[PDB]
Structure formats: structure tokens, C-alpha cells
Image 1 (cartoon, chains in turn red, blue):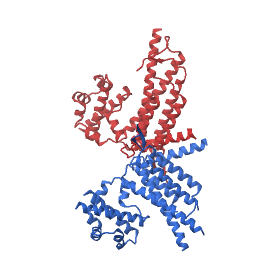
Image 2: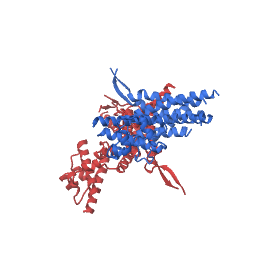
Image 3: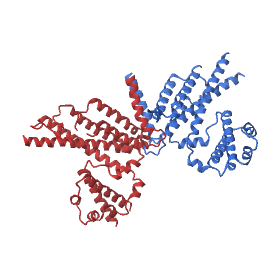
Length: 314
Length: 287
């Protein structure tokens, strides 16, 4: 009963913070339910997985993750539209009907991968540098890590696609719009603008000419590009349509080249303003799974690389 | 117990999860505040459990649902908290600390009164007394919480030019009289229908807001007289529906604690009133 009351109280605790909009003073100076849920999902990931060293994830930790995510996603079971079939039947909303199970499957793939850290990990830490045995890893460990890396590579890519898709369906706040420069030229700057409006264009060649050396330089570029697209989409026609398309092409290259880039000013604006509870759960859950899969991928990459140095050293 | 513990955890998740949508099941957040959603859910739970209410015990199955679902609707208030000296401590907010326990008590007395169904007459008399205690105690809490809730701008924008315009010339002339007795005031008016009583309350509550937002001595007297009349109406007509200022405050309130307090106290007042009224029928049918 005590362990039982404690369980009920835990659920009550979680749903109260949500219903309060995070405002524990009571008087709803809080956030919307949609933002509360968005925040809760990202908070839970930070609590379960932390900053992520590659480490064992014991079964009890997998259990907290599973149930707490269950609680947070369960609202989506109640998000409904009516569809013809002659009758009108209630059906889960079309943007969640397959997306939610698709996300839960990526989640399970990720956990199943992290579960394989329960064995003998031959690497250790002293970002903390990772080391492997002087001879390098044993072959069974090397093969496990490659498989694990393949698995999280898959999750990262599928969750990034779901994330990008949901953000594309979320409304742009008037607050973002009023902040926009007057011009695509004004948001890009004169040098970048000239390049993107060139008669002949290769987005790979466009980016090689740029200083992309820091995470902050890339995010800056992304922010200017996204602004210019909003500016152009609201505004020659043939030619506006071309620059828009080239911009969207660069935005797609950035996601591939830089999967761990922070969220853009537009992303954050959409999230803060969004009142749609389904999209909030979609956006936050996909982002969380993409981000964890990316971090795990990179960390495994760190170990396999230093293993490559050791086999050359030995 | 394992499967029985699983079933309740699931049922409670469902109700909570549903409330996050603020009654907008399309999921677009088109939706009401969590405070109003919680207010309504308490209202609709009571109507489902009790409906219109003869004088019998509540079925065991309904008692258990009532208990369970009110436990869950109230639980949010456990987390409404403030910093106070005692060292500093974190404590349940002062308007909830004693009031929520007090209301749960009144709830239990109500259910007990119904459980207890010619010194038939003496029993029945006993029952009216303790349900009368409940009606008045719940009403005091309800009235107190409403006095602490913010008046919406929409209500203010709706207001007449002044207190005379709001009351009508005849009622304004009576309330501003040089001597005044509220009992005698009311005795001259046509109080023969619910709308007539309700329209009076609404007109009087509007004058109070008009006067308070604006001789100073005179307006303060008039305001005070208005208030004594509203106290008399509460006691003469315990079954009176909510005023438009009441309804406006509820629709607009974002405070979760006050929402739960107002709604729970309100359903307990009216439940109490109905059981009182239903006992009065048998006692009159007796006479």
C-alpha cells in the first residue's frame, strides 16, 4: 500500500504540475497545457539520460522512462477527429494516428540499444576523454558497438524527419513576424544574398565559401535563412520561388551536416506559442529521441575512433 | 490487489490526460484554462453522481466513484504552496490549507445523512438540522472564495453608466433613502419568481462594482446597504442560481485553487439544499 500510495502520488505529482502550467503558486501565471507537456517531455529526458559518457541503463531506469513517457503521451489517445465510413466514426487525429506509434517504436529501438551497455564495456573515461585497451577492443565488443551505432543512426534520422515535419505544420507567431527584417536581402546580408541569387547555384559550393567553423556561425546562418524564407513566402515571382527553394535546400543540408545544432529562433518561437497539445507532444518527443540518438551515435563514434588509433598503435 | 491497483492508476491517468485538453478534444487547444476545466469537471461529476436526488442511501458503487474521482480532482490542490516563516517552510496555500479539509468533512456528513435512510419526525428533524449546517457552511466558503476572485474586464465593460441606471429609479430611490431597513426594502418588491430575485441580485451586484470603482460617505453607505441586502437574499433564497458576476468570475478565473474551492463548495451547497428541500416535502406532506 505504501509503495502503492507512493506510485499514485507520483502520477498525481506529474499531472498536477501539468494542470498548474508549472505555476506552483496556484493562480495560473503558468504556461499552456501544450507548453507544459512539451517541457515535461524534455525535462524527463534530461532527468533519465542526463548529459550523456556511455553508461549502463539498468532495468529499473528503463521502467521509469517507459511509464513516465506513457503518462505524458496518454493525452494523445484523447485527441480525436470524426471521419466518414454510412456513419461518422471517431478516430485518432491523422497527424498522431501513425506518428505516435512510429515514435514509440524508435523509442524502443533506442532503449534496446542502450540495454546492450549492461555487458562488459572495455572502454572507460578519465568531454572526458575515452580510452580503450592498449591492443584495442576485442572483436565482439567492436561488432556490438558498430551494430549499436547503426541502430541509433537509424533512430536519429527517422526522428529528425518526424521533428522537422511537425515543426513545418506549426503556426508562426506574430511576435516572430513583427521581428523580421524588411527584406530577404536585409536578413541574409549582401554577400550571402548575392550568392543565393546567383544564376547558377550548388548548395554545397554555397556552404564551402562560408565560415562554418563554430556551432554559433552555423546557427546564425540557419536563422537568417529561415527568416528570409518567411519573408519571401509572405511577399519577380518565378524568382522568389527559386530563392525560397534554394534556401530550403540549404536548410536540408544543414540538418544532415549538423544534426546536433541547437533549435533555431523560429523553432523556439513556434514551440513557445503553440497551443496544440498533439503537436507539442509530437515535436517534443521526436526532438528528445533524435537528440539522444545523436548523442549516443557521437559517443560510440568517439570510442570506435580511439579504437582505430589503438590498432594502429599496436 | 495488483490488477486492482493497475485499473485505478489507468482510470486516473485517463481523467487527468483528458483535462489537459481543456475540453477541446480536437487537440488544437481551442480550449478552456485548466482552472475552468477542473471547475466544470467537479460540477459534471456531481450531476452524474447525484443528479436530481428521493431520500435514500447512495448506492455503494456510486459512493466509491464519488470518493475516488473527488480524491483525484482535489489532489492538484496539494501542490499549491507558498513560503512562510516557522526557518522558512513550504506550506499549502492559506486559502486551501483549512478550507479543503473543511469541505471534505461537509461532503462526508452529506453522504452520512443519506446513509441514515414516528419519532420518524425526530430523526427527520435531526437530518434537516445537520444538512442545514452543511448548506450554510458550504455557502460561506463559496461566498468567501468568490469575493477573492478577480472581476473580468468583460464584466466591467458591460456595466451601466451609474448606480441609478443599474438599479432603476425606484430601487435607487429606496436604497438611497435617508432611513433604511433591508427587510422592508425587500418586502415592497415583487419577489415572486426566481428571475425577479436573480435580476435584483444582478442589479445590486453591478451597483456595488460601479460604486467601488468610482459624496464618498454616501456611496460607502449605499454600498454597505447593498451588501446587507445581498446577505438577506442568500438566506431567504438558498436555492437561487448563480449571479452573472459569479458566472463571469468563474469563466475568467485562471487560479486552480480558487476554481476547485468554488466548484466543490458550490456543489456541496446545492446538494445540501436539495436534501433539505426534499426533507421539507415529507414534513409538509406530513402536515
